[PDB]
Structure formats: structure tokens, C-alpha cells
Image (cartoon, coloured by chain):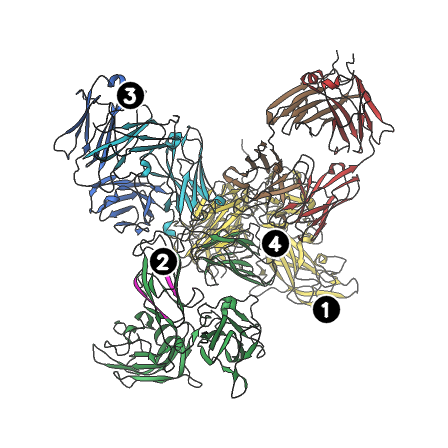
Chain colours: A green, B yellow, C blue, D red, E cyan, F brown
Amino acid sequence: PPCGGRLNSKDAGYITSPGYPQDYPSHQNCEWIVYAPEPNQKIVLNFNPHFEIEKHDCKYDFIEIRDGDSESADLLGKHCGNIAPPTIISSGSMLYIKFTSDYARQGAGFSLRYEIFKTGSEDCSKNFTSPNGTIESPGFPEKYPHNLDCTFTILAKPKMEIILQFLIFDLCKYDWLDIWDGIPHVGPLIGKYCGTKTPSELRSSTGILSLTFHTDMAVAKDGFSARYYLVHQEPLENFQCNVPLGMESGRIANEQISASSTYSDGRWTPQQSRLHGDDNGWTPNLDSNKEYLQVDLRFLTMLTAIATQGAISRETQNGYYVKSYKLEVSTNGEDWMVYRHGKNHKVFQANNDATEVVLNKLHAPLLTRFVRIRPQTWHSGIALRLELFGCRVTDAPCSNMLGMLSGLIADSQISASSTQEYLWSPSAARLVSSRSGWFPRIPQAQPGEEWLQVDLGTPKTVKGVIIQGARGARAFVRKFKVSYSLNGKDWEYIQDPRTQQPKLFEGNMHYDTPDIRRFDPIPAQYVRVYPERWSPAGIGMRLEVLGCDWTHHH
Amino acid sequence: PPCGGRLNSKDAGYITSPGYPQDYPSHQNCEWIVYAPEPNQKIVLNFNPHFEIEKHDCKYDFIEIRDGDSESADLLGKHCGNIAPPTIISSGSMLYIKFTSDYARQGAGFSLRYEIFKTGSEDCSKNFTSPNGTIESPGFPEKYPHNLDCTFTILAKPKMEIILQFLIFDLCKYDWLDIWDGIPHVGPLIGKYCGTKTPSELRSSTGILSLTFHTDMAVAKDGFSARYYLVHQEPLENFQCNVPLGMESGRIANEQISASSTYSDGRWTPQQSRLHGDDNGWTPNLDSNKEYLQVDLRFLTMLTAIATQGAISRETQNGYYVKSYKLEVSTNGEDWMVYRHGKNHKVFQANNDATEVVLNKLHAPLLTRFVRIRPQTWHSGIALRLELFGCRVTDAPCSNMLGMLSGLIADSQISASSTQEYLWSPSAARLVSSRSGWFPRIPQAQPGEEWLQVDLGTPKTVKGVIIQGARGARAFVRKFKVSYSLNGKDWEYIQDPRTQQPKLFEGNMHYDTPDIRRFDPIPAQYVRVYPERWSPAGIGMRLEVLGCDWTHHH
Amino acid sequence: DIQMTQSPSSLSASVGDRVTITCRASQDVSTAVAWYQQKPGKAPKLLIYSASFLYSGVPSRFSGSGSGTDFTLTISSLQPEDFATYYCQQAWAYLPTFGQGTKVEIKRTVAAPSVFIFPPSDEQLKSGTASVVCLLNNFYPREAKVQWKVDNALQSGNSQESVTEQDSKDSTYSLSSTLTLSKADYEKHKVYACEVTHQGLSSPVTKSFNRGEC
Amino acid sequence: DIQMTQSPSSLSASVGDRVTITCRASQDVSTAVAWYQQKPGKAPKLLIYSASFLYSGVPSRFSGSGSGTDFTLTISSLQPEDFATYYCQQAWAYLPTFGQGTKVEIKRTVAAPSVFIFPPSDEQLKSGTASVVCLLNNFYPREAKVQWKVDNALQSGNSQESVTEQDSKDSTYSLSSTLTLSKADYEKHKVYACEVTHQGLSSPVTKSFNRGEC
Amino acid sequence: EVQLVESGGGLVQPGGSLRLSCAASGFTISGYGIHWVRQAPGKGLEWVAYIYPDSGYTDYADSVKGRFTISADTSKNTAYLQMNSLRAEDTAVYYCAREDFRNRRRLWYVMDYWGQGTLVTVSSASTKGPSVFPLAPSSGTAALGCLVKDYFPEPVTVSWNSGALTSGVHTFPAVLQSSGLYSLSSVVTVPSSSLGTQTYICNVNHKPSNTKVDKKVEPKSC
Amino acid sequence: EVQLVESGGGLVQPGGSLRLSCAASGFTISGYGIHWVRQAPGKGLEWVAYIYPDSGYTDYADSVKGRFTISADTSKNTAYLQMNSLRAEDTAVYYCAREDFRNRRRLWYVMDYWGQGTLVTVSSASTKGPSVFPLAPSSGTAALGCLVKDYFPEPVTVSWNSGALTSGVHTFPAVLQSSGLYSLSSVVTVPSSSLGTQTYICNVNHKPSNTKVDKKVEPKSC
């Protein structure tokens, strides 16, 4: 019975060092997460006075309570010895406990009790179904005289884009509103907002977009008002994936554009990098190949071309421009890939002057969120104007992301052949959003032996998979096969007609930058990816499934 | 107002981070000791809920409560964040608190309240004045149905040796009895005893010898019975400091003799190293120059000669013997000095055979407690029989140690020109017993500017000083002068007749091994040592004063 | 204990006037000072914490300054509803303490009172004693003279005033004068009257009644 | 809850005999078991903790073993003073629990009882009812037959026994038989007697009295 | 919704004892600070005591130290204030207020939610239910009321037609008569056309005596 | 010296309430474990509840959970046990015992010091003081005693000559009569030569009725 887990504190419970009161084993790594079922609520822990753990200076054995979830939450306490810790009340809806044991000597251990601590706050959450409506604070334009902690999620039928736009925003410890590309703390974070930091319009085709929203009576007046729209799309076949993603049009907001630095005078800001801008452009604080213009596309986007120009100094008529550059991309803005062509990097031939435009279509389309252009050579200085071109992965017909990334596929529908940790969070396998990835028990396994499986929950038309490496000697899958099933019990491998043989799909060349693999549309409730080849570090994988719903007679 | 100190919890009090509730300063090192006036008692602390200290993982700012006194007591708790620690009850009569602040950002801090926690235990302490009597547990031979925590101290008029000898000893966490060469936790520890570890006879001429004695109801039957005697001595002038210290006679107990190792068969134990023993001798487990025979003389003794022999294997008639050796000495068994002759070490020419005895008189007498002989060359193997010769520093006439080592001179009677720590424990200046030593504020001072001073408390005949280096780049004083005074206000330097000039005494050649300096007996209530020269690390010093009481007409 | 003393201890000021209560602490208190608002017969409400931070729901017209030993509340655009008593508290020492409080009064147009006079009722006389009321409904300012006459025998030291708390809408007071005497003494006289001098009357109004009436 | 059950639930054994109480726990308890000693009408005393450790003051003749689910107390050289009831307790679960207890009795030489008989007193008869006592002072064993006769009418189901707790010095019992009847019925008869069969008498002793006496 | 409701206050003999209850709804009281603040009739707010139930930390104003004992039953989500050896000058309304300090150094010892207050009165004087006499109109706007006379202790509560009539009413502050008993009057002004064709009943209520008498005021003569 | 002294036990109506007090002398109770253990007349020891006052940790045997509330006032160095909704089968003697756990894993939940016990009796039956009748000798060793009859509740305490005479006395266990009231007898055997020339007075005491009657036993006739 593997120690640790995730407990839903709706019902008060206990957590104790494995043996307790029997002495705890050596070489031990229990971690728990205690969560309340409402954002509203807090967790409270009270320890049993009979508490014994090894002394010294907690160098060796100890208990650690952290505030939130994961090891990078703030440390509420680290204890060891014979004194139980004092009541720990969470500040969020979640707590993380970790027990550590050295390979030498032990003691009785510890027992605590968890339960929901009620603060006074109200859960004002609402789901939004309707074609158009207002999402706002209760009582807006004024203060709702109560704490709040609320989920607003927009849900859209497939083929419908969600447009969210904020009218007023008036709020980072007391108040905040984060926006999620999915279910909160399951989908990726689009961004945390607070203050009068009024957030730019968002267009999501993920099928959900949700806001978590928290307030305090200590903030005198605060609230927000937004509008949402559900606009029908129509996937053409005759459709090129080369539309501009919106530097010139502005569909990419200033908020989304950033850079390593900018000139001291502040007259060559990032927000001037928009293609065809009549006011200078982007230049950094120095000119070196260690510099970059960053655009956050917010949602997982397909990039197919880059177009760049130089810039004429509006105050001096000088002509600055980039002559060549590298491209650097990431799904989360933390893990980065420099675009390759063959073995080594790809140097893009850019401009010959300030005014004229130079286009560069990528070799093949690249799936990402954050984009960095990186100047390598230039004339005079580093000037830059830019458009990005591509389209949505959803613009293909029957090509919806089916829930791994958002959270509409639950943890319960995500299974695997083996897993390396005794007790393994199924959300670890989610494309982009998972903090690490799926690793099997011996991650250097024999091919066709290991697999990850997704239960879509009802029979769907499945048309592709998106495959990604693993974040946390960095594993990714180099080649794989796919089987599908309706019964969960009778399975067909996706066949290759040339070879007459289970088709062997290409995988990733990188632990972060994912790859879309499509195939003839088949009916399936269950899909399985079986790795065949991988990087030297072993199998590490994240996955999403592409497809759409089933639909005549007389 | 320097933060930290020593508080006597007889009256309940408060301790808070300097500013509290004003934010605490950066770069901060407050340490406190909270002590109960009876061994009997425990300390309890309760914290104020309004507790704020910097987070992260207590890497930077924190509070530490340790169980006893000093940094090497067990850690009862280390806290940081916004959660005050839970009640901490001591296990002894003392607690140690330390607050740490980084050079970056702070918070409100902390406040706690201290007071005596009553456990139930009885303080059965007695002082012993009388010529002869029994020191024992209450109710001995049986269990006193109560916890106990008691000081037994023997006090002797000067010129009287104290002899303590134990009849029965029947007791290391629940029960113990430590014996102190002085006032407990002020004088040196002679040794901690517990179990049926029946302690050997002790002869102390220090003027006090005391026992601390602790029991528990969890130990079913325990107690001890001892006898003490006060025997009059008479200091001769015609007296050589060359008496045997008691390997052959046995006045040095087996308990006191030890070694790096011993042969595997257990037939050459340390307890066979007694001079003229008819059963083999001492041999180690290997034969190498990294080996030693150790004798603990218990009290600060004067060593003047070493006599050694070899040994004939009683079971095989072979002849083993040491040919040369080095001598290694320490006042506390932790800090060691290898005896020198001129620059380099002193190799002693020992034996030429097993049977015959070889004497070696030291160059000049050496003041120590722990002695190690260290074989360098030998015939066949390392065999050793041994006598140590010398006498008591007290065997000189009017040469009593006047209280620095024992604690009969109080902290209040110990003053200095400067001191390096803002708030400076006066007991730091005590010969042998002090854990570190007296250091001035800039320990590289201008000569005659700094001084340490001892208020003997009434006008005495002072006849010498004992001077020692400092334990905690190791300071000792190489040359010094001494002034004395009756008024505390009119001061005479001890003059040198040859030079007609304040006499300049030789100091130490070592941070541990002390040196006795005597002089014409003068009347004095106050004595001052003024360092003139020192080691490269600066002034560091410990001191005792030698002398005796004032006494005719018609 | 740290003592807090408030200045002034009471004030009247017109609607829309800026208004400034002050609070001096008996020793440094950093910015750890709170302001509460108490309307009569109701629990206090937090307005300001940590010297200068508005608590939730509080009209932005309230604001606090201060930083050590002197602190200041400021109502910038005074409203009728702001009639109340305002307390500062130090939130620094182990033991909290408050100021004695500043009572704010709203200054309005002068309002002439309506004076009514009530005799006792049979029910009351029958028990033992009789009492005669004089309602001065709704007026301003509160400073109003009441005189009683019993066959013109200007009685005094045998009756009592009770004044309503200032209306937090119309900013007016009402006042009751109740006149006690034994039925023995009450029957001595027939016509009792009540006279009211108050600024907003150009001359004294006197209300009266006939004992027996019909 | 963890249940503890003790074996045997009572025993008699001679002075100097080794004696062995046993305690079986309803699930593993490591060595976390305590033994208490209760003398009648007195609070329990800790004897043994953590299965095998003597508590302070306890005669070394007591000792405990056990290690998991079975545990055993052992009094090696039984003494009269050791008459008592002995409880085991588990000191492992969040909630403590005890065994039902083992009652130890000391086996001595047979002691013939002294039988005394008391009539009622005037004081008592006057109120309403009368009661006639039969003290059997100091005997062993406790198993003793009492018979009552009222003009030889072997009465039964109209009287009550109360037995002293075994003396922890001489190891003997005393016993009282109290006979209730109304004064109405009591005057019917003159000579009442009490008869005592008990092992240590070679034949039944019968004590008696004359009503009125003088 | 965060609420506090005090109870258990009232008249009490000097030297006597009494026990207030502060009862939290909407949140768990452990892990907050529960303070008692008292206010003597028409005087300023006095801080009296507090408790922080998780820790047990309590403390008291000198004016009550040794005589008052703050405490808390968290299984009942309530805080108590046991007052003993009661003096006259303890007479006051007693508020209990919440302090939210965990993670909020700026709101330490700040009292964000206040109970409604309960009235503790300390007098050797005994309880006494009131006499309710009507104040009858004459024989535009005429006015009328009720005279609540000869009661103790405070407070009385008046209403007209059981709350139906609020606008225009004026219930006066009780004055302390020379006799030692309080008396107040409640009046309402109303149209002298709707006079004499409308039910005007005042509703006097006095918890301390358990008296309700609803008196109907009319303009009578002959 | 470590001591515990219970108080506040006695007769109580079923459904009624009662509050035991365990009062520590010699040590501070916070930072120990204070347990309540009960013992139903002539049956085994039942653990009932406990408290660890520094933390607040409490817990209860199911047989009392919801009806009993253990607590502690450390300013008074006392622990309490508030029992409510009292059933008959709660009738028992109630001991409070100390547990010393800090730094002593082997003595966890071990109860090292026990109070003297207080008797809680739960009956609809009312109090009743006793009648004391003498048991007079005859007309080596003759014996004599006192019959304490018709009382409730338990216990009665007998002594002879106010403690002066202990050796040879035998106070019997009260039996429950069919009438519902208890009765016991105390006897002492003594020399029939020192008989009739020696004061023999028994001293019966019954707290529950506040009765002391010291009855003098003589051998009387005619």
C-alpha cells in the first residue's frame, strides 16, 4: 500500500507515517496532497501530541508542510524531534505534506488529522453555456461585501470559438484573477492578472476557457466586468495554414509582445515590432546575438512563416536592420527549442535594408506557443519588425483536441502499462500542461511492451495524436505505433498500406516541442500509443488525442 | 542595548526580536539562555500568535530553540514564516534561543514568554561541611518514590584534601550522576556516570567537589551511597615534585587508563600498563606511530617525569618493548599538545629491553590532566609499562587555586578592558573550564591597552597566576605583566629587580597547555593581567589566580 | 498601556464639508492604527486599517493619514448618513486600546419644531401619579428652551428632557419634556401649557389644553 | 477499538507461589502494554510499562513479558499484600483500553470462624422493623454456609450476606448475615439462633439468644 | 456569511457572576482572534480581553484581570467570557469582535466583524415590568404616542402595528428618574384626517420582565 | 509532590448534568495528558476520555462521545469532565490519571498517577440519611458493632472513637436491600474484660445527607 496520495478533505481524515505508532521505515518518501472541493475553503491540520522523529538538526528525518500543492509552495513548517507542530491552516484550498527518512534509525513517527477550515468566503462560481453573456464580479460595479473564491468557466460546443473581452478590470496577494486554457490547475495557465492590469482579448478554440477569481475584504473596492461570445467556425478543406497571427492586425496584444531588453531612450520598445509600423521598431539595449524578441501566442498555435523588416530611425533617418536570425520556440515559455534544419541550427536569411519585407516559410509547420526571433547578423544595429503566420490546429476538419490538455479527459480516463513512481498522477501524461511526463517503471523498456492509453469515454472519430517529450537526461519518444479499440478489449493497430504492417509514426526531436500526427479517421473510444524508439534517457511522453464526435436513414 | 542575554526564569518574562512589533533589523544574531534557579525545574515557552519571519525555506531568517544551553544542544525547533511555534517545554533546567537575520528584507518578528514549568520532581540538594559523612540518595538502599534533581557539593577549608569514595552505585537518559571539579556547569566535568558504572575514588584539592544527580520514576530501583573525608594536608617547602601519581599504587584507577586500541586476544589491555605488572602489559591492535596509551589524571596535575619498561609475553616468553616515544598532553582531552624541546617535537629515549626501567625527567614540569605516551620506535612490537611522576599545584605553600577554575570566583568578579562580543559571558575567561577564552574587541590591540581583571572579593595573599591560551588562528598570550590593588583604584605593577621595571612574564607556547607563573607574595583583592605579546591570531586568554588567605600582637 | 486621545471630541459641520478628526498616541505606534465608525445603538464598523487603508465597502470619501504618534481621519465630502462617533484604535501593543471618540454632527438649515402637548390619561391618574408630555418634533439646532406653566406658576425642577439622536437623513432632532406631579397636586389646576423658544421660531410658541375638555 | 481479554479472570494461590496472569490483545500491539494493580476501594497503581519494564517502587518480584498479541504478568513469590485485581492496558492505539481484570486470592491455612449473634435493639423495634445479625469473624476459605432458625422454622429468602474483602495481612474473611422481619412477626417467637457450617469447624457451631434475657 | 451573536447578558447582583457567549456562524473560530470590547452607557469603547483558541493565548485589560476568564469551545464554535466579582462600573454593552491575523501583519489586532452587543447591568435594584399609558391626540398633522413608565432594567423596545408603521416614529431615550426607575415615550406623527379611522397600537416589549402589552391609542373624551 | 484530587461527583437525576473536577498539585497540567477512567460498581476499568491541554487534543470512548466534554483551565491547573444526558450505566467511580508522554515513547498512554476517584451515581431515587442502631454484646473475646440502616446513595463511612480504634474492626460492604436502600454494619472484636469499662462509640458519616451521628454501643439489659 504505497504511502502518500491525494485526499479530498470533503470528509475529515487522517495521515500518519506508514507504520504509526509502529516505528517508520528507513529510506522513505511519502508525499500527500490534501485538497478541499471548493476554492472557497481552506485545509486545517492538527497533529497528535505523541510525535517522535529523529533529532540531530532535522538533517536526516523530518516532516514538511508546504502551502498549496507541490514542493515549490512556501514552507509552512519543517519539524523533527518530539514536538508535534502547531495547527497549520492553509491559505489556499490545498496542502502538501512530505515525510523523509534516512537510511539509519527511526521512531514512532507522526499522525495528523485534516479537515476543511471555513473562512467565511462565498463560492460564487458559475458555468456559462449561452451564446453571449456577461461574466463579472457579483454586485459589480461595486464591492460585494464578502470574500470570494469563484470559478467561471465558459464551455463551448465543438466547432465554436470562445471570445472573451474585458470592459473594466480593477484589482498580487489579496486579489487576483488567473485565466486557464482548460480546467483550472489541469489545463495550462494562460496568465495571472491583478491590479489595473486589464487583460487583452482572448480567442480560445480549446472548448473551454475558465477564470478563477479571488477577493478580500481588505481590498476596499474591486471587481471586473467582461463579455464572452461563442462564434461558430467552419473548417474548410481548401484552407492554407498561412494566415497572419496578428502583429499587424493587433490580434496579438501588446501584453503578449516582450523582449530581452530595449534601448535606453524607450523609443524602440517591443510594442513597435509590429510589421509595417510607422514608428521606429524593436531594438535592444545592446546589440548582440544574446538578444531576442518574444511573442506569446497564448494558445498552442501552428507557426508556418516568419516575415521581417528593418526600420528607419524616425528621429534621425538612419537605417537599421537584421540580416539573419535563429528561431526559438516553447510550449510554456520555460523549456526552449532552437529550430533546426538538418543537424545544426537554422540561420534565417532576413533583410537587405530597412523598408522592404522578407518572408521565410518554415520547411514544415511548427507547433508552439511562445516564439523568439534571435538576430545573428545585422546592418548598423538590431532593428526588427515582424509578422508571424500560421493557423489553429483546430482549423483542420475533425481535429479538435479531445481533452488531455484541457482536463475534459479526467485523470480516471488516463491509464498506462507501467509507471515509474509507485503511485502515479495520471495528469502527468498531459500534452503541454503536465509538469513532467509519463515515464515507465524501467524507462528503458523492450519495444511494444509499454504503452499509454486514453479513454475518451464515448465512441468518437479519432483522426490524430499530438506527441510530446517529458520535462522532468531528457526523455522523448522517437518512434511509435498506435492501436485503437471500441470495447476497451478488442484492439486494432493503425496499419500502413505500403508495408502492410503496423504503421510506425515519427515522434519528437525535442523534449518540449510537440508534433502532430494525423491518420485516416477511425472510430474509437480507447486509443493507445506504444513507443518503439526513444532518446538515450528512455521513454518520456506527453499526449493529446485529436478527433471529433460521431454524427441519415429511413 | 545588545540583543540577547541570560535570564533567570525565577520570575516569568518576555523575549522578542529586537524591534518587535517593529520590523527586526537585518544582519542579526540574538542568542538567549533562559534558566531555572533549581535543577528540579524546567523552562516552558509560549509564543505570541502574531509571528512573522521571512519565508522561502528558512534558508535566510529563522528562530531556533535548542534544549539545554549552547548551540550543540538538541534542536527542539526551527521556525520561520507566519506560524508561531507550539509550546516548547525544556527537558533540563535551561533553554537556548537564537534568532538569525540575513542582509536582505524582514518582518514583524516574534515574541515569547518564558516561565518555570514544574514537573513534580523534588530538589533534595545538600551542602557538606563536616569532616566526614555519607553522601547518598534519599531513602537509600531503596527507591525514593519521587523524581529527583539534586546538587551535592562538598566544601573544604583551604589546605584540606577531599576524598570521595563510592560504596554502591546502581543507576543514560533517565538517570545519571555527573561529578564536577567545582560548581556544576562552571567548573570542569570530571565525568558523567550512569548504570552500574561504579566510579573510582577521587582526591580533589580544588576546595570543592560536587555531584549533580537525577532520577526518574521510570527507573524501577536506583540510588547510590558514597563516603567523603576531609584530610588535612601540610605544605612543606622542602618538597620535591616527583612523587608517583599512581599507576603502580593504583591511585590512578583502571577507569582512568585507556588507549587507541588493544590486541585482539584482550591479553594486553591498557589496565596492564601499570609499572612492574607481572601480567604482560599494553600493546595495541596494530603497531604504528599512530597509537597511544592515555591516562586521565582527572584533576589539573603537574607532570615532572615518565618511567617506562617493556614486557615479556607471559604466554610465550617473547620480549617486546618501546625504544622511543613522544608525549601528548591536554587539559580537557580534546585539545592536544605534543611536548616540544626547542623547535621540533621531543623524542624520548625509552627502553633497551623488556624488564629494566627507564626514567625521563621533563626539562621543566608540565601542567596537564590527560597524558598520552606515543611510541615511535620499538623492538619486535609495542609493549608498554608506565609510571607518571609529579605532584599537585597545591603542594607548593600558599598556592591554592583561588576560584576561576572552580566557580568560587563568580562571573560578577571577572572584568575586562574590552571584550569582542557586545554582551560577553565573564566565565569565558576561566582557566581550563571556559569553552573558548577571553578575546578583546580588536584582538590585535596596542600593548598595555587591554587587560583582564579578577576581583578575589577580600584581601588575599596572591602568589601566582596560571595563564592559558584560548580555544575558540588560535590566540594565546606570549608575554604579559601583572598589576595588583587593594582599593580596586590604586594599582602597582609587579616589579622586576634586575631591570627596575614592570616584570614581563613568559606566557604560553600553546593555546591549551597552561603555564604557572609565581612571584613574591603580595597582598591583593584585585589582580590584573596585561598582555604584552601574542600569537599571530591576537590576544586570547584564560586565567586562574594562585594564593591564599591572610592570617600576633599584644 | 498605550493611550490614544482624540481631537476634537465633537464637531458639527455642513454636508459636503471636508472634516478632519485627529488622534494622538501616547508613544510611537508605526502605522498600526484603525478607525471605526459607530452609529448609536449599533456595533462599530471598521473603516481604515494600518493608518491609510480603506476596508471593504467604505465610501472612498473616507481616508486616513498618520505615521507615528499623530494620525488623522478625513471625510472629504460629508454626508448626513455620516453622523456617528468615530474611534481610533492602536493595533500595535499586546493590548489594544481606543480613543475616547469624536462625535460628528451634521449642520443643516434651521428647522422650526412642531410642538405638541399631551395630558395624562385616566388609566395613569388612577394608579397614583400623572405626567404631561411636550413633543417638539423635528428641529435644528438641538439647542432649544422648554418652559412649563401650571396656572402660570412657572414650574421648574419637576420634569425631564429626552433628546432623540440626530436623524441621519433629515439631520433633525425631536425632544420630549415630561412633567411629574401627584394627582393630589394635579387636580389643583385646570389649564396646563408648554412654551418653546427655539431659534427657528420668530417668537415663542405655546401649546396648551383644558382639563376635562368636553 | 482494540480489545484486551485476561486469563484467568480469577485465581487463588499460596504465599510464595509463582503466579501468572495472561492478557491477549485483539490485534498486534508491539510491546505497548501496561499493568496496573488495584486493591479494593483504592486507585490503581502502575506496575509495568512497555510490557517488561518495572515502574518505580514496584517489588522486583513482579515482572512482565509479552511481545505482540499475548502478554504475561508474573508474581514470582506471592505475598499476602499482593491480594488485588490486576489490569492490563494497551498503550498503542489512539484510544486506550483495559482488560476486564484478573482477581488474585491468597491461599492460607484453614481458619475456623468465630460466630457471634446480635439481636435487634429497642431503638430499632420502636420504628417499625427488627434485624438480627450473625458475625462470622475471620475465616478461610470464603465458602461458608449460614442457616437461620426461628423456633426451628428454618427461614430462608428473608436475610442477606455481606462478605469483607480478604485481609491483606492474615488473608481471612469476615461475613455478616442480617435477618429482616416486621416487629409484628418478630414477637411471635422467643429464641432465635444462627448456625454455621464451614470447613474449619469439625461440626456445625450454633449461636443463640433469649429474647428479654433478664 | 460571517456572524457573531452574543447572549447571556443581563441584570446581576454586585459581587455576583455572569457568563457571556459569543457564537460564530460562517467560519471556524479557532485560528482567529476573538476579542471582547465593552462600552459603558454613552462612553467610549474599552478593550477588555481576547483569545486565540488554537494556541490558547489569552490576555486581559487590568480593569478586569483576575476577575474575568475568556475561553472557547471550538466543538461549539463559541467563545465565552466568564465575569466574576462584578462591580457597578462593569455595567456596559459587551461586543465580541473577530480579528483575522494569520498572514496579515497589517490587520493584527484589527477587529473586522463585531457582534451585536449584549447588555450587562450590575445593580442591587430588582426587576420591574413597565406600565404603558397612551398619549391621546386633540379634541394637517396631529401626533400621538405611548408612555412606557416605571421599569428596570434597560432596555425596552417599542413598535407600532408590529412593524407595519415605521416612517415618522420617534422612540425616546429612557431617562433615569429620581425614583431609580426608567421611563421613555414613543411618538409618531400622522395625518389628522387618517386619525380616528385607523388602528394605532404601540407594541411595548421588555425581555427582563417577560412583558408584552400592546396598547391601542385613541383620542377619547367624555 | 504530584497529586490529583477529583471533586464534584454525586447523585443525579437521569437525563441530568454533572461536572467533575480533577485538580493537579505539584506539577503544571499543560504538557501532560489528563485521562478520565471510570469503574462501574465492582466491574473493570473503562477508559472514557482524555485531554492534552497545550495542544487541545481531546478524544473520547464511543460510550460517552457526544455527551461528555473534557476540558482544562491551566490558569487553575485543573481539568474538567462535563457529563450531560446522564444514563444509569454511567454510574461509577471516576478516576483522573496523568500521562507523561513528552520525550518518552515507551510511556505514551501510560497512566502514572491516579486521583482518588469520585463517585457518580445516576438514580431517580432520592437522598436519604441513615438510621444508626447499635449491636449490643452478651449477658476471652466478645464482639460488637453498629448497624447503619436505610440510606441512599452510597457511600457511608464508619469509624470507632474517631480513629483511635482501628485494629480488629470490620466495616461490611453495603448490600442493596429489596426496599431499594442500602445498609451495612461495622463490627469490632475486643476483650470481654475491657468490655463494660471502656467507651465504644462508632462514628457514622454520610456526606450525601450531611449526617453525622456518633452512637455509643453498650451491653444493656432490663
Instruction: Locate residue D168, reporting x and y percent.
Output: 74, 34
For the residue labelled by badge 2, is the local secondary structure a helix, a strand or a loop? Answer: loop
Q: Are marks 1 and 4 on the same chain?
A: no
Q: Is residue B136 left or right of residue E216?
A: right
Residues marked 2 and 3, same chain: no
- Residue E143 sits in which quadrant? top left
Which of label 2 and label 3 is nearer to you? 3
Subunit of label 1: B
Q: CA distance from mark 1 to mark 4?
A: 58 Å
Give the alpha-carbon distance from disc 2 to disc 3, as whole Å.
Answer: 66 Å
Q: Mark 3 belongs to which subunit?
A: C
The residues tagged by marks 4 and 2 sit, at their Cα atoms, a distance apart of 43 Å
Q: Amino acid at mark 1?
A: Ser
Q: Alpha carbon of mark 2 to alpha carbon of mark 1: how far?
A: 84 Å
The boundaries of the magenta stretch are: A161-185
For label 2, the residue is A175
